Image (tube, coloured by chain):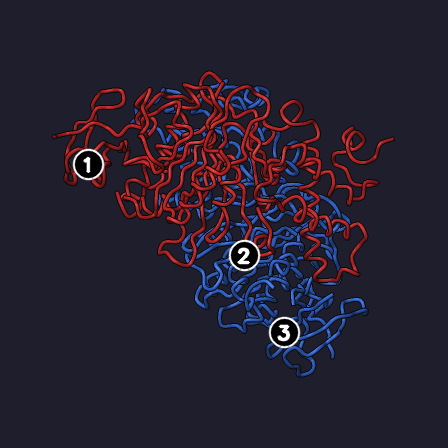
Chain colours: A blue, B red
Amino acid sequence: QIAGPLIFVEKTEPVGYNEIVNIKMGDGTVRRGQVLDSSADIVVVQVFEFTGETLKLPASVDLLGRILSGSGEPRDGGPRIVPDQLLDINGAAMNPYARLPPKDFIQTGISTIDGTNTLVRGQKLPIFSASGLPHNEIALQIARQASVPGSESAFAVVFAAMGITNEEAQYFMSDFEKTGALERAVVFLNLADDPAVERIVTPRMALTAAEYLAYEHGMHVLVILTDITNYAEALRQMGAMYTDLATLYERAGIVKGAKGSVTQIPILSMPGDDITHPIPDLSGYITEGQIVVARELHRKGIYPPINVLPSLSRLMNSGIGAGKTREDHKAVSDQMYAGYAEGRDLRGLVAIVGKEALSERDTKFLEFADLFEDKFVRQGWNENRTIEDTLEIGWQILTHLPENQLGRIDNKYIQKYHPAHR
Amino acid sequence: IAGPLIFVEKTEPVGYNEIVNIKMGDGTVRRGQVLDSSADIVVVQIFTGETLKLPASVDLLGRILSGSGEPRDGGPRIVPDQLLDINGAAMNPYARLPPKDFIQTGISTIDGTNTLVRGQKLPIFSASGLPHNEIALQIARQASVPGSESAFAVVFAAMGITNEEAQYFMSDFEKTGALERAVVFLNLADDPAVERIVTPRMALTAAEYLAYEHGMHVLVILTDITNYAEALRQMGYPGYMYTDLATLYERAGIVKGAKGSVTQIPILSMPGDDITHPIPDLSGYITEGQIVVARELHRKGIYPPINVLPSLSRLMNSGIGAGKTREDHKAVSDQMYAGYAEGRDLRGLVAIVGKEALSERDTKFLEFADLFEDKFVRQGWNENRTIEDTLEIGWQILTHLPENQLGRIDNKYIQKYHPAHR
């Protein structure tokens, strides 16, 4: 009973609980069977190591501009979905992923990720959050801001929602259209009242969309997946999941031809006390780092309440330095990392020895931390700060420190750009 | 608001919002306003008392205390050789210098891949109903620093624990004769609210007195923070609960004189089905790395089990390498991590497609992940692994990998280590 998989067939013939199916794969050779659960249109299988095509997504460039269900049903009101191609969703049978590392920077436009732990083409960088926090708000901002600068390959987004409230539905369905962010993105909208199975096929159909656009066309796609704790919830439940999620997080990367990529940012929250878990081990997703939405910053009323230094990007160096963003980048990042860390420490012995007993030096760091969260972290629902707006904002507030104790900034960079030497 | 909290030796009962004069460990005076009255401790920011001081001593090592009252072992309360204020005014012992020369914990997934360096703030990230205190003890009985001729002490502090938990913490410290190099403070889930939040501050000051003043590399385990949190809230507008939290995480680093160190491995838990708040925000404690305890790995029946992909040690580079450990340390760490990171993706691939249907290269990377969890992660609870043993078996699970293709580490280490001889 321990066996993993969970493949999605499409109901062609009426089926029954745990009947053997033994069917398909997108190449013509198949093995293994046994139904687990189903709905009016689609069948979840699950297997071990009649009949019976794998569920396929209507593949077309005309997807862009449309708004879909977990099953890809025209939710935007318009006509049907006339498909150029028609491909297997459930981890496909395409595997368009080249054995290469991720590379070259993505401009989210928000500085607490672009400038301090940069999202890189073909990464998985989850938005580590919690109930109440504005992680959806901070997500669908970067849905209409993001781009790949100077990249010869065009850019595309796949926003995907899993079992959201039917009210916050036509919210996301409006923050697009208005901005014109839609006519660049395919949306996959799942509601809490949609058949529970739909929620489990919402990520696959999203991921499958991204792969068609990234490989068949030579594009850079970003896939945001809001509230993956609703996915874990949807799964009847656990066990024996841990491999089932690996089918999801495997589906990110740079494609063959190195002329496109699948880039992944899911949001992993936790509400308070979970039902019959508490959920989970989503730690299979963070393998390349994560970004941290914090309550501490939210509470004192700053946006986005992102906390650097708990946040991490492992592949940052593979899309940062010379002729990608700017040379000084990593060197500016080290100082703000260290200065905010060393400054966040001095908020401590402020409260242990009063605001005095605190050397002049330390008052600058103490203040830098204030300036850091005021200028650097704080950002409008919009201001699409480019890496250059971001990096210079950095120097703008790095000038509250003295020098030499800026020991992570290479003198070659201060003397080049530091607001004291043109 | 600033408000420098300090803990006062209660003589006679004092009301709320009373104004008080209190002399320090360094007898002075204070801006006295009483916040809370409890046991033989009052929290401030005949008439107007003194201050609660730790009786610091060279033979504090070997003893079991708590906070107020004091010994839980029988029983001659320590004769001091210096009385010291608890919240960190005492010395003050910290050098503005980077953490340096590494601690051997005997646990490979820490040592091998996320090294613990003399002067760190490496929290353990875990969840309700996982064996963290269990792992805490292991590193508590095992820890040492091969090389440098400076003694190694261990301060162990427990907060809000059950009598049973307390029963087997003590029993373990005396069976191993590890209490001979260790101080132990255990606050009980039933002890005064004050006696819990004074707990960490007694441990750290005791640590500081030992590190400075005695030139020893002291390690402080703090188990666990969320209970500190989930008590700090019910005793004691503002939103402020941090700052006070910052008062804890500042108290780390290598001391003036460079002979001692205060390394701090606290543990923080994601709350489970029992309490009210179950968040909160202890984000500020994660700024030099983390070591995540994976639920998935636990219910695969593995101990530790810490996941290494989310695991991080920002200052690993400072502790590893030749003379400190061995040349090949980073090489092996980088290749295991990459090897394991891959293996876990392929688990997703192997599900979607089938083990019969993935590449021979991918097979021996899929199986590596099994070996990694089965022979690297997996550890006995009385297993002390010298880095030699860590890297030795690290090199074992590596031979399963295609020698004749994959390196990222090639140069000199593959020929000098690894079976290949001539």
Question: B227 and A146: which one is in front?
Answer: B227
Q: What is the crowding at mark 1: few (fewer than 14 residues within 10 Å), some, or many (at least 20)?
A: many
- According to the picture, the residue beneath numbered tag 3 turns out to be A36
Q: Chain of mark 2?
A: A
- Say if residue A367 shows up in the picture: no
Under circle 2, the secondary element is: loop
Does residue B285 appear to the left or right of A48 in the view shown?
left
> Sequence-wise, which precedes: disc 2 or disc 3?
3
The quarter holding residue A372 reads top left
1 and 3 marks in contact (CB < 8 Å) = no
- According to the picture, the residue beneath numbered tag 2 turns out to be A180
In this view, the residue farthest toward the right is: B422
- Residues indicated by labels 1 and 2 sit on the same polypeptide chain: no
Disc 2 versus disc 3: nearer the observer: 3
Residue at the image position 62 percent from the left and 37 percent from the top: B113
Coordinates of residue A262 in the picture (x, y in percent): 66, 52
Dot 3 amino acid type: Leu
- According to the picture, the residue beneath numbered tag 1 turns out to be B34
- How many numbered marks, from 0 up? 3
Placement of the N terminus of chain A among the 4 image quadrants: bottom right
- Mark 1 and mark 2: span between their CA atoms? 58 Å
Coordinates of residue A422 in the picture (x, y in percent): 54, 21
1 and 2 marks in contact (CB < 8 Å) = no
Query: In this rendering, is residue A247 above or below B208?
Result: below
Q: What is the crowding at mark 3: few (fewer than 14 residues within 10 Å), some, or many (at least 20)?
A: some
Q: What is the crowding at mark 2: few (fewer than 14 residues within 10 Å), some, or many (at least 20)?
A: few
